[PDB]
Structures are given as structure tokens and as C-alpha cells.
Image (cartoon, rainbow, N blue to C red; front, side):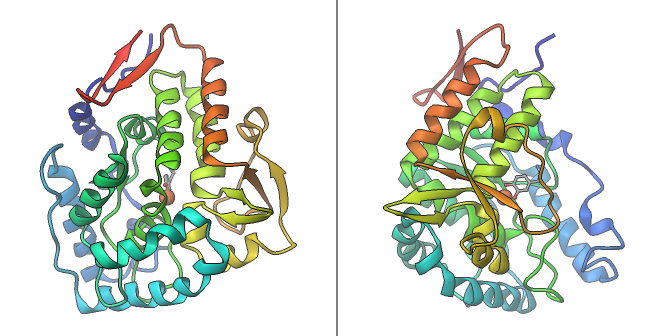
Length: 308
Ligand SMILES: NCCc1ccc(O)c(O)c1
Ligand SMILES: [Fe+3]
């Protein structure tokens, strides 16, 4: 039968009891695996996420000097590339994040301040997430303009590398785009298409998500710029994606939806969007082909999904 999905924004609280409990930091391969302090610090951030409930302010955390040093290294190194590689929407908002959210080399911004700023721009809000959510729950949150965000940071032994999302990736990669109204509507359309969709389509939407929100390129004037969070938080791939090496294809969902990708090396190919409004339209058309015995609409006044 139709798989369950949240109908009010508060029902998102039901996701905490549905994450992968044995996370990446438990693998022998993780940069912080033999470090017991790092291991305890991760447990500490996971307990904060676990106990969090919709509507509460996100807890503030005092980051250690070692964590701030890792943040500073990542921040200074990536910052040099945005003016020439990042899409206009990213560069337009960055100064405001520096002024009101504390985006600076010496300070890790607190999620509550960032979430309030996003709320004022487009109504997006953040909630801390323990570990790995299923694609279904992760995309479902977007229908409500809710982004599940990590609050921990990568291990300091390898500042320019992370095998998973961490706070540098969320703040430098995702957050700036969620400040833009058109990108916000586009992300939300992906989430709405996902509600009650059969598993095999959830995987298609997760693949579309990967080639847009995480690794998307966008047309701007007669140029091409990065807007994908995974590119914007990766020093090496951001430079590589705008060089002559990768193959570039126009965003076509029927095709993008089944494309294979790897998470371990630079992407051999990227899809280019004409604009976020156009990508939004393509998602809405694609959602029409998903076999669901109903239709959905979000009502921002009461924060509930209406099932038609
Ligand atoms: N679901 C696979 C892991 C994942 C999901 C969403 C993201 O934004 C990200 O950076 C990584
Ligand atoms: Fe991400």
C-alpha cells in the first residue's frame, strides 16, 4: 500500500527513529576512527540531533579550538574560488552571511542563527540530523522547506577531505542556495514529488537530486557556473568542473534520473540547468509521471500537506 509520509511539519519528528545507527565514523577507514575524543564528540552531536523536536531552538555548541582550526582552513581555501566559479545567487548572498551569521575564518556559525536567517529569506529552516536518513525521509523534509543538516565537523587530520557531509559542507555548500527564492521553490518541488512515491521512483528523485542540488552546473549569461553543494564545498572538484575535462549535458530528467554516478572520484559528467525556474518546471512535469493515486499541495499558512 502507499508508503507513509508526514502530513504536518511536526510529523518530521518521526524521522529520528529511522536513521542508520552505525555511521561512517565507526569504519576503520574513517580519518577519525582511532581517535576516542573524536568518537565521543560525534556521539555528543548525535544525541543533540536525536532529542531535537520541531519548534525548539537548535542547541548552541561551543566548538573546540581544534575544530575551529579545521573550519578556518576549509573556509580560507575555498573562499578564493567563489568569485569566479560560484553562481551569481551564491556570491550575492555570501556577504550577508558574513555580516549576520558569523561566516568568518575564526568562528563556526551556530545552526540556530543560520536557520533564522534562512527563514527570513525564503522560509527554509534547518534541523540537526544524527546520521544517515533514508532518501525517502531526507527528500520528504524538503516538501516543508526543511533541510536536515549535520552539526559535527570532519576530523582535523584531513581538513580538505570528508567521506560524508559535515558542517563545512552544509554551510559553505548548501546554505547559500537555500537563500534564493527560485532555488527554494525548485528544492521544494523535488520534495513534493517524493511524498508517497514508490521506492523505485524515490531512487530516481535521489539521482536527480544528486545531479542538481549536489553536483549541478547552471547557465548564467553566456557562461557556466557551479551551484551544486558538493562542488561548492570541494576545492579540487570546483576547479575541475569548469575546466575542459568533464562532459557537459543539458538537464533532461528522463535521462538524468537513470544516470549512474560514483561518490568517490570527480564526476565524469555533469548536467547543466538553464535556471532554477526552468529546473523547477521540469521536476513538476516529471512528478506528473510518478504513479501515485493522489496529488499533493503544501499550505504554507498552516504548514500541512493537502492530499487531493
Ligand atoms: N543520501 C546520501 C548522502 C547525502 C544526502 C544528501 C546530501 O545533501 C549530501 O551531501 C549527502
Ligand atoms: Fe549535501
